Length: 350
Ligand code: SF4
Image 1 (cartoon, rainbow, N blue to C red):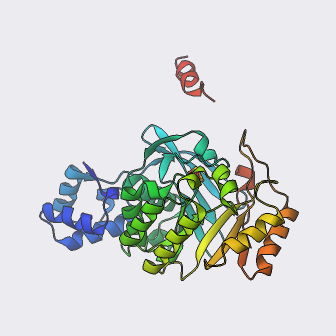
Image 2 (spheres, rainbow, N blue to C red; image 1 turned 135 degrees about the horizontal axis):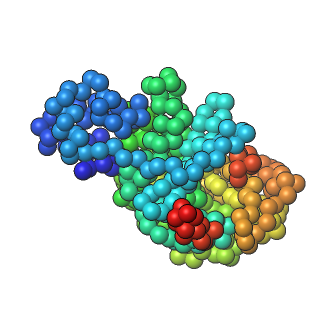
Image 3 (cartoon, rainbow, N blue to C red; image 1 turned 45 degrees about the vertical axis):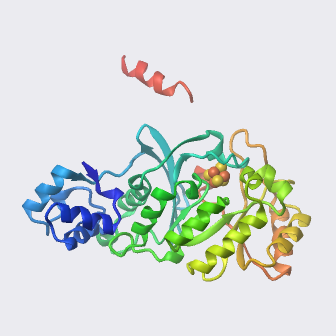
């Protein structure tokens, strides 16, 4: 059975044609899937039995399942999501005017960024389209589908710190196409943001495939620091990454001219005022908005949290050069064993 969550609108229409159905039936089923978060053909009431029968034989709608849910007092929701026998994260961050979903692109990651908890476990595999868009679908079903509640559950999707998306371009791009589709989640290209640590040839490729908002996972004011913090910098240095960013902005207007620059503040490693002055000089030819991230250590992380006074001084330095600078909020602060699986088998035996 084909999982319909693997298909963009064009592919859905091609599949429905091969079942002897008119293209617009594919569009209709898409709306049920994404506007109503429906994974059950019986519930699709304006589809006839014959078509319902065809789909149940050759197709299904199977989104990744929640294995854990944590809910913050600030409304943030974090999910551990089963993708096969592997696990990934999905985070829902509601605000008064919008709701952002952070989704995973890979199971683990191969880039070895030193501050990243996703890195420490290493790279396992790429996610399929159904596993990426399925995170959005699952989040949307739980929060409340657009046409069930009358409100878009999600206005923004981000891909950051949950696998390098540019190393999973085959699955990431169609997933984003469904996010942007009116019959999918109907998000503006300005509100689908792909963060990358700078896989430059893949970024050149991204701009030829799709127009979405780009963020750059920079985290350092110079190569010698970034070489340490973000090892991929050894292969593609800052100036090469920035040249690639400018090339991407020739092809895409989702950023409206200004790339988002992400920068984790790491205690006495990259958060000094000297580093801020260097960053300002570095970004003089790159129109941008700078997002400073008050990063917190995971168990055994090689860095500590920067104080808010150091972060605020770093920010003021950047603002004195005229950069738009945002210190990001920490969300879901209240929610932030190797034997357990075997231990559960033994306990359930009794
Ligand atoms: S590219 Fe992103 S997910 Fe991968 S190790 Fe670096 S910060 Fe973590």
